[PDB]
Amino acid sequence: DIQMTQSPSSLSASVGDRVTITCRTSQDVRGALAWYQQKPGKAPKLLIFDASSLETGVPSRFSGSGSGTVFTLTISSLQPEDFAAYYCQQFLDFPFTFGQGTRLEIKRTVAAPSVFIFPPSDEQLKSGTASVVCLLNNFYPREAKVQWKVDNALQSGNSQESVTEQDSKDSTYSLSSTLTLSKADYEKHKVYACEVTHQGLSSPVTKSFNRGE
Amino acid sequence: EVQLVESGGGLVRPGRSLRLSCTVSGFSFDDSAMSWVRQAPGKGLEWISFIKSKTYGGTKEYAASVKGRFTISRDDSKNIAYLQMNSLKTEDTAVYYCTRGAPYGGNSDYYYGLDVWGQGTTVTVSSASTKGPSVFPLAPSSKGTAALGCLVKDYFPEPVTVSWNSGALTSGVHTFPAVLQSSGLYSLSSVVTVPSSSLGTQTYICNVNHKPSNTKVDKKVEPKS
Amino acid sequence: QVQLVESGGGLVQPGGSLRLSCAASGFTFSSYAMNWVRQAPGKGLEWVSLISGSGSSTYYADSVKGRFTISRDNSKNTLYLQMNSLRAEDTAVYYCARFHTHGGYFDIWGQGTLVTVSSASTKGPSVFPLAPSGTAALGCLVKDYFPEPVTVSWNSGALTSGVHTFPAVLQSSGLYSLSSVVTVPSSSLGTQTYICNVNHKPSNTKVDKKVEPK
Amino acid sequence: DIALTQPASVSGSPGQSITISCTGTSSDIGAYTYGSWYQQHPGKAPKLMIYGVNNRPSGVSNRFSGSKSGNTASLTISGLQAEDEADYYCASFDFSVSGVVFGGGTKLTVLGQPKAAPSVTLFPPSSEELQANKATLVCLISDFYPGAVTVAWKADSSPVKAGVETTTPSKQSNNKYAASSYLSLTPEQWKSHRSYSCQVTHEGSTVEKTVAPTEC
């Protein structure tokens, strides 16, 4: 079996930068790697069919290089249509495993997130499950820590996170944190708080709601 | 020209069986090797199975993750390929892609990649039946740009359509990705940014359309007293 | 390490056979294709023959298409090229080459064997000592050698430094000439072991000559 | 059909990258071609430099890069050293006809070398050769660069041309050129003149090594 390591997981670039992605294989594959490109929702296509050769339906701006362990994909002038997910696949012997996956995302000015706390709905109050909603609007970069605090005590293991794709207008990301509590759990709290930790924020932004206000 | 369309898929239950078909047009089936690739929703690409041509031994092989539960076969004179799954696990919900392996020269046993990819068909394994979305309002109580939101809980299967102002408000509308709750249903969040003066001027109307259950939920978002 | 060795060569009267055998170790001989590459003396490389892994897929070049036959023996783990009707033009170094699984490139090359065709007969080297007349040079001269190559080992092979092997000389008469020089200390001349060995493979002449100060 | 063409010779410098282009020609070339670049030191087995367009083999220096532009392929060597003195060949493998065709090769000559005067060794006719009745006067030229040094044999202080054979310059392993000159003389001729000399012209200079018929 051939283990495949993809570096780096996330690439930030603007138009015109030269981006290099490295696939590292423990075994010596020697010219049996293929680089695939996947737009976020569509089918993938084969970009580099050898470790270095080009297919017909591929622009000349994609270059490949490789030696045994280390294979590199190089984009010289990053046109905006190349922002996608890039995967590597080995072909020396079965199984033809796929790499972890590298993402390319627009680099924009570091914008701090706006944190909004939506308290449990009155309609869902009698439903049985109380939902607390934490909305992060206009965030950059992707990394962001959302923590739930009940009665000033941190909580974990009951949180769901949803991350939107890169905005096609502002080039920002939005984050949704959902905390699901039972009716008893919802009643048993006094104050519910969302703590946002991010690069843009000077300090951990605390959005609090009184459980009964 | 070179076209692969996969058919089958849909919702199935864990432990049962299902059978995906792949139809090809443009290139000869007999000497072209085929492969099956799987994408977990949100995870990376995973390689499932490989079938070789009839003239290269006709061997069938799989990744170790699905060996012993998956069988891939190819039918000549019909130009189609079968994939069979037995004892499906909860984890195996994914988009399945049918690919053609490209031999190094015109012909050879050794391949360099998978050139042509079908659109892929979706396979969801679950236990819940069709449950129409429950729409709950998240009203803007802040106080600027305020957030009005709809939370759709317990929907299945994906996806649902969220419209702001009956489709009017397409600016500032963020539709969060579907999240799989442990209860088996789906959860979606729709958020809209409105001016503070506009918060109390117009009426926030959210339309939730769920095709699987035929649910049209009209939620009137108002400030919470 | 993975090794390719070539055996079978020398002087062939035009029309001979000279079955060459390349023996290979370190890689599964069954699964890889094998090629033969011929280099004329002073000219470039060119391709002669290709054998696939399973056999029965034989591809020759244009110049030879009804003369050279190629057989791989996985049981004996080697591969043989047989020539028939070998013209005067096909005198060259023959290189054994391996094709990788993902074919196209010659992964490993053999050392090379020399195939010469000429009506001239093999003439054993005549070895004469050019005696040394702080460090001084003295050596051996081999005259009338045909064809190449001749191994000139000074000091029974122990000597490794200070030995310059002059390039072969193409004499006008049709024979060859070669020279080997050794740099030994001027004070060490009266005590050094200065004995040369000349091995001429084409005629199988293994001569041990002794050079002494004059 | 397929055929290759390579430049006659390329020259660079000991600190600069140079490119060598293999140009491929074919008629209606819809075929699959796999390209490789091979290195050949003088009188040694060729070694695989590049396969595909930019694949380097293990154990091979990362200074060699390759590119494919349309049909023409290119080898780029950066950080050129004196160790890269060799000939480079391009090989195209055609899967359909299943044949590999080589090119004419390029001589990668560097200029970063100094002009060194040759060392000339003259050897008197051997005693065994003297008994043999034919005298072979040996002249060896070692450690010269650039390699074009003419040899003149002088007998009795006058030029002699009969029986003189000169071997072409050969690249020694130590990054130098060497050559051999052999003068064939009759045994009576060897004991005819007072002294014969070798005059070597390497680059402008003239080195004279004398040996007389008074070897005794």
Image (tube, coloured by chain):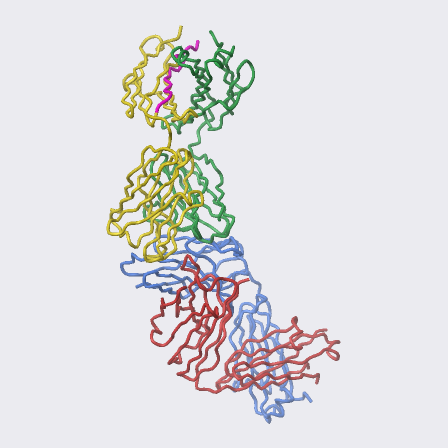
Chain colours: A green, B yellow, C red, D blue
Residue D49 placement (x, y as % from top left) = 47, 59
Q: Residue B225, relative to residue D140: is it above or below?
A: above
**Residue D74: within the magenta?**
no
Q: Residue C20, relative to residue A40: is it above or below?
A: below
Q: Main secondary structure of the magenta part?
A: strand
**Which quarter of the figure is the C terminus of chain C placed in?**
bottom right
Left-right relation of B202 to C20: left
Q: How many marks?
A: 0
**Which quarter of the figure is the N terminus of chain C placed in?**
bottom right
Return the residue nearer the eye: C91 or B116: B116
Residue B211, quarter of picture: top left
Left-right relation of C191 to A73: right
Return the residue nearer the eye: C212 or B125: B125
In the picture as drawn, the residue positioned furthest to the top comes out as B225
Residue D102 placement (x, y as % from top left) = 39, 65
Q: Is any atom of residue D32 visible in this view?
A: no
Q: Residue A82, relative to residue D9: is it above or below?
A: above
Residue D69 placement (x, y as % from top left) = 37, 52
Q: Is any atom of residue B65 visible in this view?
A: yes
**Residue B143: within the magenta?**
yes
Residue D101, quarter of picture: bottom left
**Span highlighted in magenta in the image:** B139-155
Residue C188 placement (x, y as % from top left) = 74, 76
